[PDB]
Image (cartoon, rainbow over all chains, first blue to last red; front, side, top):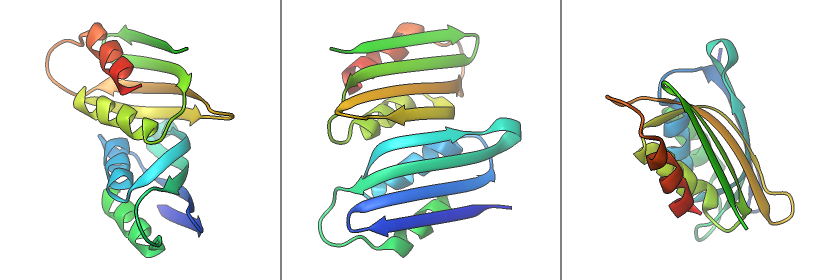
Length: 79
Length: 79
């Protein structure tokens, strides 16, 4: 049971992820976020009972328009 | 005006940071955390007004002993 939710309005990006935690998961998520040129402005994340729940609010820092499915793809690749 | 607090108990690590937010701050912090081989298990972070507040609980993933001043120094450079 695992969900990836991406909400995009102009340059504002909301990310929610729920999945089974495994080692270095949070690191892969933030690597993905870095590689999407997303600037994180707030995060709540924890993994009680080995199940990660993550909520991130971010802003797009690169050039051009945001491609939401690319965000969704990178997160799914990270978990 | 900035505060960095690092607590180490065996392999558990608790980081708290308060400083002025600026662009890509969160990314520099997680870059630092990655390069310290810390596996992040929980994060609460936000910057209401321009002032970032951050609490991270992590576990050391590398070999050998944790070197606490390493963590605090890398965090200070990330600011």
